[PDB]
Image (tube, rainbow over all chains, first blue to last red):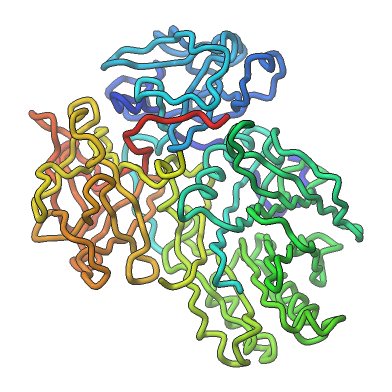
Length: 154
Length: 261
Length: 153
């Protein structure tokens, strides 16, 4: 943007697949055919707003945006909704000692969990999760986007 | 000594849209575990983790900014700390910033300029732990043409023309995005034997960037190795993928420099 | 704790984790998603360490202490030995962020079948072409270990 160093080109948001560590099932968007791998891709963008600070719990507020559209993952997600609808599209990344992530909704401070295939829920996990340990149901992996890829050669 | 530390480097490619998540996803992983870095150089760091706290220590005696912060990677009750030496160079967009994360506090901090660091390029930011000095750099994107002046100037500052006798006994390591192939930088340094014979470039043979290019590595001078014998160094470089538990949130891969087992 | 951070899982595009099935040494390695191997325990978690050689790595089982080793057309796990080249692998980056695991001794990559009429994938070694097909895939994700996690916020 108005960087002091224009020689350094701005970088686009990172592409990821959000998988439950229990089922290894990726969170899908409704923008592509569920048969299309692009249906498992999201852009990780940080939320800069300040209306969720009281329950942030030391986590990092983010949004999972559809690639090439102004739509974001929303919890009771048939699919996605307006990125402008923060109350339903803003999530909270909570770090762990293993590299897995606990993900809470910014609004309620509830934990997103998956107990089995196609099972996705938002349940109260207390006032704070710091120092507490959780099972795979509460864990999410922010991994490479599902699909094809090419080996990088030097 | 340099080989006593596990050094790593990562161009975070921060920006106003995505910066904090990169710190908590990838940086946290690079610093953890038995193989976590003792010192991690970060380029294009944007903002520091929002939980980082600036200390009262003033380590900025020049014009280029350099501040010390502490960052708790663990809980309040069970802390896990590291120091961050932040240089907010990008006053325009605050994204092309340099930083050095250290588990140990720096005995001293340094800023070393090249022939263009006060024109358009970025200076080397560094810290000293005992008799070892560690610098992070981000050379110009167009071939990293400022690299040679940057290495040369650090060399004359500590090794050839030190302002105190101790400095000649300091070992130093310049780590980061050189924006040019190791062999390309190596060829250029050979134009200056004094610099070239007192250093050793340490880089991976695997790509360090999505384009397939090798751009992130280190160049060092071991004060306990004779001129023309730096290649005796028992430090090897390699991609630090053994530290990841997530997608790498930038186009640059983390690179580590560790003592040969 | 401080030891968990040392382990991870190598997850295929199908969510299948490279794992030890038969605990006895020198038995083939397979791939089972966590959902269908919950009783497997930590034999599914691995510690990546530097090999004997600079840019190479070896995988040490969290539960058994054994190492992955290239053997024949597949992988087995055996006693760790830095002098066994077959136990050193290259973690090749890809343009998506996933990795391709290459055997230094063989020069072939860890291949698997994302699609299976069973709950597990067969793991083999073959020409490194970064294929990503329903029955032949060579890409893995360096992911969190299958362990309970403690929030460090």
